[PDB]
Length: 108
Image: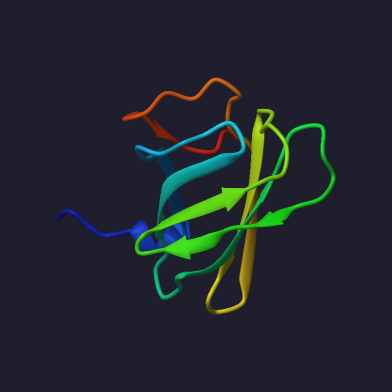
């Protein structure tokens, strides 16, 4: 019959980034969806392109916001840490030109 080998695949995490009304040149607001089986997102950091200093995001309600003293340059990098203490890093998840109302997931 239809056997369930989904467990064979092992574990998987689904993360997506969506810009919300309010994005600015020195301030960026994006909604983040993190789904992990038995785990959950605990911390997220955002690093600007051409920059080597990851900046922490503030969890606002159900989204994350980051403010810089200069203009943001894409592609942007975002690192995720699961409450269980797991960490995941996504490079080039959002390009410099982002649109509002469109989702944006991290590429391989």
